[PDB]
Image (tube, coloured by chain):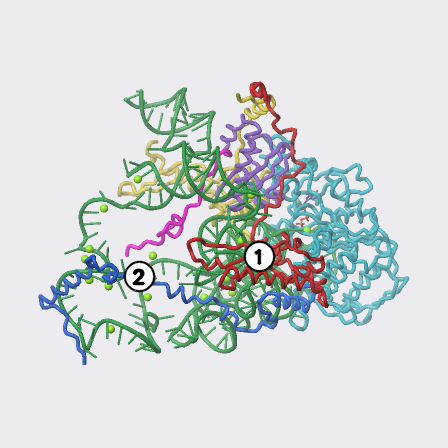
Amino acid sequence: RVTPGSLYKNWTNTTHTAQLQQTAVPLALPIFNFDDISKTLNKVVSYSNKQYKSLHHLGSFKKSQFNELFQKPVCLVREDATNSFLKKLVSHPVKKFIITGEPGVGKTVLLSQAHAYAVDSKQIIINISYPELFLNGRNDFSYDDDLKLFIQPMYLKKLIRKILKANDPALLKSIELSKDYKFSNANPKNASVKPFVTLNKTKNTVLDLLSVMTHPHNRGKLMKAIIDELSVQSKVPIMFTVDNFSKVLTTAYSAYRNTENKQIYSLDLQMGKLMMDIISGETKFANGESSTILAISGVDRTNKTLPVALGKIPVDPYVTRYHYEPKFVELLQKGNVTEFEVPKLNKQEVNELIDYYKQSNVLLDKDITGKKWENLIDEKYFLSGNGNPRELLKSLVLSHR
Amino acid sequence: VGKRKSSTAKVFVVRGTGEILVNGRQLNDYFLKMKDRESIMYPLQVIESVGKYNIFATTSGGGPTGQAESIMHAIAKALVVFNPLLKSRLHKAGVLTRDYRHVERKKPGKKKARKMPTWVKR
Amino acid sequence: YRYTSYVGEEHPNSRKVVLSVKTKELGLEEKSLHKFRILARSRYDHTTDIFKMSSDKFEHASQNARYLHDILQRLLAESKDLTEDDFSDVPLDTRHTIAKSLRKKKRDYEFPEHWKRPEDAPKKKFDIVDQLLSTL
Amino acid sequence: MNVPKARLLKVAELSAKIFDQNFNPSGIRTGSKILNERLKGPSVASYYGNPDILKFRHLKTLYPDIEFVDLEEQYRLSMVEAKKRRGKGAPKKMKK
Amino acid sequence: KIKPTAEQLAQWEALKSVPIPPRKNATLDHITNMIMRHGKKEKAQTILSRALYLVYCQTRQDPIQALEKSLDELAPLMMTKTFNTGVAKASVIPVPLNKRQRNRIAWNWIVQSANQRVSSDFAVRLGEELTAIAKGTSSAFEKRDQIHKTAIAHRAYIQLK
RNA sequence: AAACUCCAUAUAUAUAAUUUUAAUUAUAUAUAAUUUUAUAUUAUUUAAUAUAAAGAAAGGAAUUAAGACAAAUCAUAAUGAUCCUUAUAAUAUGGGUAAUAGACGUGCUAUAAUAAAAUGAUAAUAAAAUUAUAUAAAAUAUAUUUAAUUAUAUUUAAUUAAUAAUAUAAAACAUUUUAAUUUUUAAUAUAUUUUUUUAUUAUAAAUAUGAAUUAUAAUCUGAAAUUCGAUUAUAUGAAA
Ligand SMILES: Nc1nc2c(ncn2[C@@H]2O[C@H](COP(=O)(O)OP(=O)(O)O)[C@@H](O)[C@H]2O)c(=O)[nH]1
Ligand SMILES: [Mg+2]
Ligand SMILES: [Mg+2]
Ligand SMILES: [Mg+2]
Ligand SMILES: [Mg+2]
Ligand SMILES: [Mg+2]
Ligand SMILES: [Mg+2]
Ligand SMILES: [Mg+2]
Ligand SMILES: [Mg+2]
Ligand SMILES: [Mg+2]
Ligand SMILES: [Mg+2]
Ligand SMILES: [Mg+2]
Ligand SMILES: [Mg+2]
Ligand SMILES: [Mg+2]
Ligand SMILES: [Mg+2]
Ligand SMILES: [Mg+2]
Ligand SMILES: [Mg+2]
Ligand SMILES: [Mg+2]
Ligand SMILES: [Mg+2]
């Protein structure tokens, strides 16, 4: 008893997935570029078209945000938060960050900005938004024999596709291969004719490698090969990113069960192990400017692990595996992860946001009409808990109290 | 010091730019319900002085909404010292009144305070 | 050694005696101190560096006190041994203390020092008759 | 628990040796909780009262000079006498 | 001796003209209370505000105001209240309605019409219904019209007149 | 009857070397209101409404008279009369009070998405009360490959108590999931909705509700758990 047009989903899903961004005012806002941050240092800025294209593919813009409020997802540049982070990324020798903060402070937004910057500066981006998919057991998996770990060839395929599409092909096909690669063919065409697909050293490309389509049991092998290729190449920078890395840290054991009924460890998987290797000084990328940018989510569980990894708490040895996994900490220490605290909004920034919202026509009538502007701003600041952006946004729009 | 239900809120209000700290942590972190935050703000909102006064609240006892109400009550009293002419206005707004609403005890024969067990005729 | 006595009554808690010492105040070297603390286990609190223990096993209070003393002496002897038993590589178990802390409440938070306004404080108001009076 | 198990066990054993408390690493039913329970008998016995309490009988022993009267007893005796009089006295008890 | 300072006096004067701000939008609060069941007001509030957000998204104009307008439209200005009438014919009379009663009648109808919509989440259903009413389509309107017609019959049954 | 009374409230004073700390408290002693004042608008100097300024000022408990109902109690206990005195008095071992056609009250749990379940350790937020016929912390072991949870066992740290324990309150709020529901899934492509979209293929009246009833295995208390107790596990999964 359902039509195509009617809304059948729950609220959060509906807001994400039903395009109510359709009925919205076009806004001629400035464009996000790191080279011209001096112009737009503390102003709202729409992303470039190319950036948007890349960012959507990656999975930067998420469901629980209020990206439905505008024509397209929008951020502002911040001197204390985003700009400083970008500068650190540019300058630091290690280039290896974990974006920490309170729930709703704007970690994902920071990640999205970092991605956009990377896109601008001719870099490949391997984004893993929501590791919950590979960590929790809701897709097929298999123990590979060559690689001593469990591969996940539904998730992997999706990730490969994202990598292919998020990045431009000219940058991606500038990379020649280091080794030759045999794979099992899995086209609808040439199934009987071509039993195997072969990629040569100099002739073939990374783009071509990505476009390969194998059976599930070779997908993990393909992924491994791709990563190796990217590590080897020194022509283009590789930005690796993992958002909701908190889940990964806490969920040490996956929901998958091996032959004997017991839970599989995250490092015994392909994806989680690979990710950990990337984080640590192990799969070292040949080029400079090649970063790993991790991000915590307030959604996920909290425990002693991440604080212990960083310069926060001394290592209590007696706390349990559930609330403190030491292997993960050790791995984090190995690859010198310098954490980045996202600061809460200043008064001026809050004011600027409120002004933008007013321009876009999100503010309620009781806020605008018959009220001093400065007083309103102060109230908004108070209700957000002194500049938590999400909370502020909620107070503005989702209050109706 | 303000009170409501079982809650008690000792609140240090000071002239610095308007930031909040409830019980040694951020306001949005402590009070999750926006209503409680709005209530807390209200003494500063009846005056045009939200943003003017720094507030350091310290609560104990009761639940969250009651705690927030006790904080609000305390803040109004604190404000009254800064400018005595606004005291009447605050009273009119309904912030200077200590909300007496006290939880009624369970009486013997009754199940709860008022809720009696079912009656029968036959 | 704290002793308790119920005056008119004959309580069975009058026998209870409680020894209690700060572990740093005990005459020990650093290695031996750590070993002593390890041996104490739940009896040693780490936030306050205090080790206490009570005995109710024996009939009289004096007996119980003597027993506690003997235990303490034994503990000290063990701490000062060091022959084929150091306990350098067993970290201090602080689980009981954290459990106790959780059970209780905390008021660790304080008023921010940079939020203070000495300039806004009420200055001394000039009372002329009081000044006149003060001839001493 | 990165710290080893055997060392912890040894430490626990040592602690047990130091104090009087026993060291049961295997976790077997020893029977310790049966004996170690404080015996509650004297308190239980002392429930109804002190059986040696002064009675009316004694108020003759202590003070022979004062001719006391137990009123309830006297009443009972009077009732018995009345019963005897009106043919409602107790029947004579069988011996066999 | 009171001794009020100049700045304080100026502040008081500035305040004096401004009226005391209201702590709640009353009609909204009433609605939230009606939605609410087991002293779980927060959940009811979340539901209501989410619905209003959805409404706004669908049609970009103040959601609260639109809701109030809808209530005003829908709320029947009077009701044909039944009476025993001294043990005789149950002679009905038109009776004027308090604001709350008016909006209460409207809300129940709105809820009913929402419950016919598809989604699992009630908040979504509610929002869709509110948007439909804003645009101008419901059986609630028809019911109101019918009520008004029934009130119109029994003109002079009103006692004081 | 009201009032004095108790609880709770507001204020003041006293005391607490602010390690028995919660001073945001506890407890003795006061004071405080069955609130006051004024301007008007109706009805006749007053009384209800409204407005204003002054106040923290707003409840609950106990107390339920005379008479009556030959209301209830001789099974709390006692006493009158009457009846039993090798028995209608007294002690032990077992059984019964828990029997089951229909019926009648009180409750509890339910019949799923404005509502259920997983999770949430710099442990979100209480109060009141108990612990020498005790309260039992941490930790080890087994159920259970990690560990947590829950349940037992092992063994008693602390305190007979503003000091330790019962006891990290729970809803809340947040992520995840949820059949009925082809209102979803997964194979392909697809893309500026990517924890997602579109296209084309295949996905065909009690559940992934409920927890009655029963089977087996363990555990707990006790000397003893068959009639007849309480847990846990693996199955069973009515009715609604
Ligand atoms: N920094 C920043 N954040 C914003 C901006 N606009 C919205 N946000 C908010 O940033 C939030 C993302 O915070 P995040 O740290 O991902 O929340 P978490 O997932 O709970 O950790 C969203 O909820 C947005 O509402 C902006 O312009 N800048
Ligand atoms: Mg996130
Ligand atoms: Mg009276
Ligand atoms: Mg204190
Ligand atoms: Mg009477
Ligand atoms: Mg009778
Ligand atoms: Mg009678
Ligand atoms: Mg009798
Ligand atoms: Mg009798
Ligand atoms: Mg007998
Ligand atoms: Mg019975
Ligand atoms: Mg009854
Ligand atoms: Mg349910
Ligand atoms: Mg324990
Ligand atoms: Mg305690
Ligand atoms: Mg908890
Ligand atoms: Mg049925
Ligand atoms: Mg079930
Ligand atoms: Mg259930």
The vertical placement of F195 against F218, above or below, is above
Nearest the viewer among A339 and F191 is A339
Question: Helix, strand, or loop for circle 2?
Answer: loop
The chain letter of the green chain reads F
Nearest the viewer among C42 and E60 is C42
Q: In terms of secondary structure, what is the magenta stretch mainly?
A: loop
The chain letter of the purple chain reads B
- Disc 1 marks a residue whose amino acid type is Leu
Q: Residues within 10 Å of mark 1 (few under 14, many from 20)?
A: some
Judging from the image, mark 1 belongs to the subunit labelled C
Write the start and end of the magenta stretch as one range: B94-122
Q: Horizontally, is E87 left or right of E123 in the view?
A: left
Q: CA distance from mark 2 to mark 1?
A: 42 Å
The vertical placement of D71 against E10, above or below, is below
The chain letter of the blue chain reads D
Question: Helix, strand, or loop for circle 1?
Answer: strand
Q: Position of residue A323 (x, y in %)?
A: 65, 58
Judging from the image, mark 2 belongs to the subunit labelled D
The chain letter of the cyan chain reads A
Q: Position of residue A125 (x, y in %)?
A: 79, 53
Please check the rendered image and state whether residue B97 is part of the magenta-colored stretch, yes or no.
yes
Q: Colour of chain C?
A: red
Q: Residue furthest left?
A: D86
Q: Which mark is residue C19?
A: 1
Location of residue E93 by image quarter: top left
User: Can see residue E128?
Assistant: no
Q: Horizontally, is A72 left or right of A383 in the view?
A: right
The residue that label 2 is drawn on is D53
Look at the numbered disc 2 and say if its residue's Cβ is closer than 8 Å to ligand 9. no
- Disc 2 marks a residue whose amino acid type is Ile
Q: Quadrant of the N terminus of chain C?
A: bottom right
